[PDB]
Image (cartoon, rainbow, N blue to C red):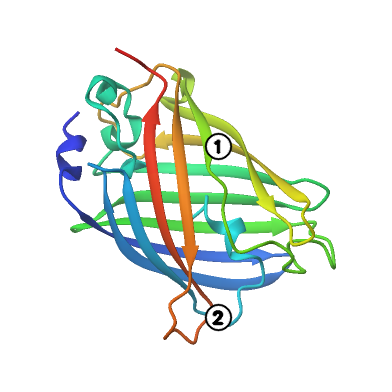
Amino acid sequence: SKGEELFTGVVPILVELDGDVNGHKFSVRGEGEGDATNGKLTLKFICTTGKLPVPWPTLVTTLVLCFARYPDHMKQHDFFKSAMPEGYVQERTISFKDDGYYKTRAEVKFEGDTLVNRIELKGIDFKEDGNILGHKLEYNYNSHNAYITADKQKNGIKSNFKIRHNVEDGSVQLADHYQQNTPIGDGPVLLPDNHYLSTQNKLSKDPNEKRDHMVLLEFVTAAGITL
């Protein structure tokens, strides 16, 4: 994988999201940096259209798996870096239990020296006074595993996983993710054996930021293939 050479140091990240949830149009811009050598991402996201009309935690998975730390013995299974710099398309359906769903289409690729994640998001069938449109989710994030499988027929990867979002009444709002990734270029990519990504997230606020925003620190580590 030549693409791996692009991630030996810290790389600046740009995230641009345009969204439409039940007809609500909104935009998010994020800026920060990622270091695949320790799997660490640090970004700040701002809603550029006013108040974010869905909860920030529900956008974390949508807002760059090429920064996952793959241990040396697993580097042959790193589809995400192998697709670089031309990049890959990442598509998801995210089903919120007892509520609506997101459909997302993103391109992840290098634009100059910056790794860019550009996303179109559509949300439909969300409930009035539900946990999403009513902003009833806690501002926090649980640790999760996302298992990755090869999708040979699409020359890409697939993944299905559930996110637990804590509700402020102590209940949990499940978000069922179905993901597929396909390379943008025609060059060879690494199709992996089964494995998983272990992800942790810390959400915070910038005390000097007056816009609706999210400060995010994320660790992503590949696992599940031993020596």
Q: Position of residue 148 (x, y in %)?
A: 47, 27
Check the image and report above or below for 62 versus 69: below
Which residue is more in the foreground, 147 or 22?
147
On the image, which quarter does residue 75 sit in?
A: top left
Q: Is residue 120 left or right of residue 208?
A: right
Which residue is more in the foreground, 204 or 8?
204
Residue located 16% across and 49% down the image? 9
Q: Is residue 226 left or right of residue 105?
A: left
- In which quadrant will I find the C terminus? top left
Q: Residue furthest top?
A: 227
Q: Secondary structure at mark 1?
A: strand
Q: Amino acid at mark 2?
A: Thr
On the image, which quarter does residue 198 sit in?
A: top left
Q: Position of residue 105 (x, y in %)?
A: 52, 50
Residue located 19% across and 53% down the image? 10
Query: Label 2: which residue?
Result: 49
- In which quadrant will I find the N terminus? top left
Can the viewer see residue 164? Answer: yes
Q: Amino acid at mark 1?
A: Gln
Crowdedness near tag 2: few (<14), some (14–19) or many (≥20) residues, C-alpha within 10 Å: few
- The residues tagged by marks 2 and 1 sit, at their Cα atoms, a distance apart of 27 Å
Q: Position of residue 115 (x, y in %)?
A: 28, 54
Q: Is residue 109 left or right of residue 127?
A: left
Q: Position of residue 71 (x, y in %)?
A: 27, 28
Check the image and report above or below for 43 versus 10: below
Q: Secondary structure at mark 2?
A: loop
Question: Do tag 2 and tag 1 residues touch (Cβ < 8 Å)?
Answer: no
Of the two numbered discs 2 and 1 on the same chain, state the one appearing first in sequence: 2
Which residue is more in the foreground, 193 or 205?
205
Q: Which mark is residue 15?
A: none
Check the image and report above or below for 121 versus 155: below
Query: Label 1: which residue?
Result: 179
